[PDB]
Picture 1 (cartoon, protein in one colour):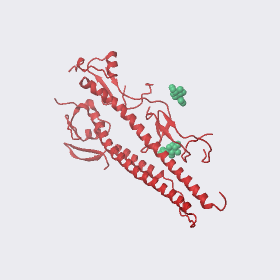
Picture 2 (tube, each protein chain N blue to C red):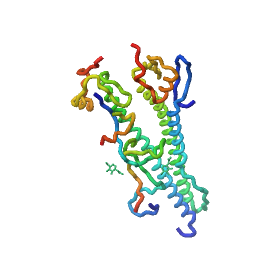
Picture 3 (cartoon, rainbow over the protein chains, first blue to last red):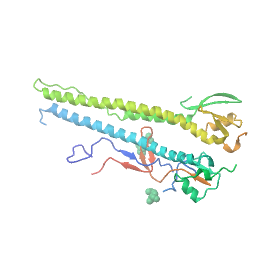
Length: 41
Length: 97
Length: 148
Length: 37
Ligand SMILES: *[C@@H]1O[C@H](CO)[C@@H](O)[C@H](O)[C@H]1NC(C)=O
Ligand SMILES: *[C@@H]1O[C@H](CO)[C@@H](O)[C@H](O)[C@H]1NC(C)=O
């Protein structure tokens, strides 16, 4: 948001996005070699 | 800073810009390196089930080549429960031919 | 022809060919990897040098320390980023050639012998059209069978 | 008769970058950068 911040704050960075994957590659009778079990929730 | 402290103001600015570049660079690579590993982690885990299961089923199934196994001996829901857990009883089942 | 691939021998001849799908994906990966290392570095106009009087020794020392400090940080990071990335590049390549080995083993299934040296031997005669199929994801398992 | 081993997929459009890949769609993701005030 801004580098001149007063308080107990997160580190300021010049990046636009920092996104961690937590999940699987989303690749939507056949097993994983195909990929895509949308029916398994 | 006063107008006669330009070198000190510049020292302060450089110190702050320096730390910002360090933290930005580290944030960018930590995210990319961690994401590379997260996706490999997940691929490894699904493959590990495939072999965990293949190794208990041994010779009583066909590998179909598409991430599945076909049983030679009839396998019902109680068998399914066993295979889906670490309890498949190899000795009770056999190949037909 | 490429980084990963096939070698074959059959009634019609022998030779080498790259697995273009596998090589191109690995290639693009390495290219993106190199670019991540280089493109994420921030380049700005800088002059670096400062002048101090003889009555500003603590300020000159503060400036020197700040500059030496950042240099040690960037040098250390450069050294480990290169070593960590090289460890992964080499594991990446080993993984990719093994992945072809199993990608192929799983389509050939029971119609081949595993020879234990990174090759397969066919029970049924397999010609250049078969070779093309195996070298792609199109091997037709049902059309071939074990002799004994 | 048949048992398969596989994995989850959904309708998510969250994307991440990795060292080797760019714009990889994932089933779940977490944004760790605060953008608003
Ligand atoms: C995606 O799937 C979830 C869970 O079934 C559903 O609630 C949501 O409406 C779907 N569509 C979109 C655009 O999120
Ligand atoms: C990733 O997606 C963004 C947003 O659409 C786009 O600007 C960028 O060029 C894409 N990068 C690649 C490598 O596809």
